[PDB]
Amino acid sequence: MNTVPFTSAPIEVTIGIDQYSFNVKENQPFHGIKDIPIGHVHVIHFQHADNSSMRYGYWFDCRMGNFYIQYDPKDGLYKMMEERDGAKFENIVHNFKERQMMVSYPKIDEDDTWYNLTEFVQMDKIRKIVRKDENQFSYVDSSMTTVQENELSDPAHSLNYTVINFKSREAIRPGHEMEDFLDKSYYLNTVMLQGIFKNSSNYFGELQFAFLNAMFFGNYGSSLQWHAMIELICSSATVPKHMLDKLDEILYYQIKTLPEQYSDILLNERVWNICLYSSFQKNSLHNTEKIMENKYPELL
Amino acid sequence: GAMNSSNYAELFNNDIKLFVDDTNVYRVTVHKTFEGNVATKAINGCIFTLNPKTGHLFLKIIHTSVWAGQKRLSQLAKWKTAEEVSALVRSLPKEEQPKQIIVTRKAMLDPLEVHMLDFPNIAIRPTELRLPFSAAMSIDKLSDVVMKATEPQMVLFNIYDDWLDRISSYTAFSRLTLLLRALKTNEESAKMILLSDPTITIKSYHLWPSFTDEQWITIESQMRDLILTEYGRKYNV
Ligand SMILES: O=C(O)CCC(=O)c1ccc(F)cc1
Picture 1 (cartoon, rainbow over the protein chains, first blue to last red):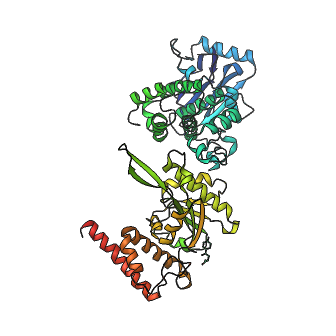
Picture 2: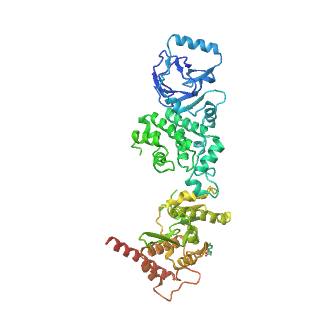
Picture 3: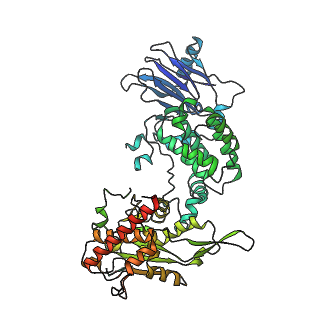
């Protein structure tokens, strides 16, 4: 297990770590989070008590370096930093661990929730969507726009998700207009899977990353991207069978984890009714259909 | 966006535009089979593509062979319409290409948009006007060319005859829409009004009779009376 220490907590803040969250009071003696399960990406996220504007956070992998959080009073946020002095770093954490100034990542042993939400998410792929090459971790916030959103405005601060547009020349072969618009299999399998993503694992990783950015930061363009990537699969008559089975599992855990009180805003009625009841794959998402019907029957 | 009554004068400005109506593309007769089921038989159709400023009607005749062996014909019909309009715009030189194409039914929007991806500068728009272009087939010469077709064919007409020599496009469109509404509301009565009098004839290349200006006023009043008369018959007014 690895550790994200904090220099301090000078401002009152709700801290997120993956799907967990806890409150820290202004100048409470907090020095971070320990026992973080190795083998997964993680996300540490922040919502200030005195200004819920700008949820923000960092995607990181403890295998890639020693990272800590320090408040910057000038820019007004908790910043992630990398410490290269490894023995310095261990020395600091051990003192914080000895004084019990760190919360423990509260992972139940039965519980695979985080694995199931991040199965295909890799740090190297995150760092290509979020471009800041000097850091091994990636900053995302509530307000960052996506490349596609910026085509319809500081490119350095943008989410470079793969653009999906059903009425674009990329999606529609000259001479196959009706075919390709009503059956997106060409766009899914040739343009996206074989051409851009190379395999379904990269596709699902971007889909899972988009969902998590929507859920944890309220990032609107991330929510658009997650729905577009679901719709493109569901709107395809020809999808490898293992892809459909895995999608059902991926979506089931996303719907299971979504806060019930955020459903009115995180779920697009049109996309979901189309995918579950009218689409080519309307019968291929049994687990997702069952949780959506039992948990959010109003949306449908 | 949509075209309506506030921006009605825009139809007659100098931006080339085309109305497209697909309501007579896929046409069928419904009949009983020997086993007592119901069966359809397609008959020839047409796309009604009209530039409102000039009166130019690009009548693409849809021959029944295009439906042979095809499924979901009502859906295919929209995409076939969009294919043909796209082919028409490609056939014209850049200076005769529309800036806007207005579809009379919103179901034509996605088909036409997808077929016209190569033409990002041509706006594809619905309209809130209820245009009676379905009654094109009540015009005898147009009906005749469509039903006689033995193969796909593009037949060209001025839907205003030579009215633009004496009236504005705005007025010519108003006249056309009143005539077509009347033909749509009571076809037999409308044709009676138009052809009651034998000494007013239809010139060899024209669709409508050669009414003088004063006779057109009389005809227009009779057409209005017909619409009002049918509206009263309908609603018991
Ligand atoms: O403007 C006129 O009066 C003559 C030309 C004309 O009526 C026309 C109609 C259809 C077409 F495709 C091309 C020309």
